[PDB]
Amino acid sequence: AMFADTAALKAAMDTALKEHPDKPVVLDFYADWCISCKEMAAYTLNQPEVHQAVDMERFFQIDVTANTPEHQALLKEYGLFGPPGVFVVRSDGSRSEPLLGFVKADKFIEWYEQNR
């Protein structure tokens, strides 16, 4: 489910990386004004070929609609002003360049596979 509490989010991400460091996690920045976020949700993230390629139990979403300081802080730490923004985040600490808009499943998957 979508997070709004960044403390809860990091806790979940840290655990997932300790549980399977040989697998990355994915972090996705959502807001209710984000058109590409809603396209991703409707045409790509819900598609069976994505769930086959990406472990969606390892897919974390943070809702920054409220724009509280913790949201602002997290955006800046990921080099964003706002959504969209989808990162591959690895157990090493390193993160991929973000996907910054709507793509269909095949390009999403290509982006994931090429970024670990």
Image: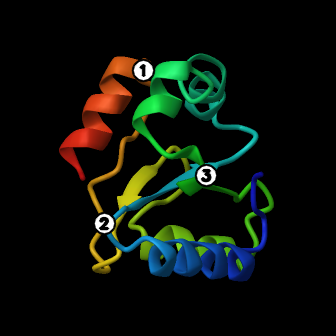
Write down the residue under mark 1.
Answer: 105
Above or below — where is 77 with respect to 60?
A: below
**Of discs 3 and 1, which sits in the foreground?**
3
| Residue 12 appears left or right of 23 | right
The structure residue drawn at horizontal position 40% and vertical position 34%, both measured from the top left corner, is: 53
- For disc 2, the marked residue is 95
- Residue count near mark 3 (Cα–Cα under 10 Å), binned few <14, some 14–19, many ≥20: few
| Marks 2 and 1 in Cβ contact (< 8 Å) | no
Regarding residue 9, the answer to whether it shows in the image is yes
Sooner in the amino-acid sequence: mark 2 or mark 3? 3
* Amino acid type of the residue that numbered disc 1 sits on in the rendered structure: Ala
Q: Which of marks 3 and 1 is nearer the N terminus?
A: 3
Which mark is on residue 57? 3
The amino acid on which the numbered mark 2 sits, given as a three-letter code, is Arg
**Closer to the observer: label 2 or label 3?**
3
Instruction: For marks 2 and 1, give the CA distance.
Output: 21 Å
Front position in the image: 78 or 81: 78
Depth check: 23 or 104 in front? 23
Of label 2 and label 1, which has the lower sequence position? 2
For mark 3, give the secondary structure. Answer: helix
Residue 58 position within the rendered picture, expressed as x and y whole percent measured from the top left: 54, 56
Q: How far apart are marks 3 and 1 (CA)?
A: 17 Å
Residue 68: x %, y % from top left: 76, 73
Can the viewer see residue 59 in this picture? Answer: no
Element at badge 2?
A: loop
Which amino acid lies under the numbered mark 3 shown in the image of this protein?
Glu
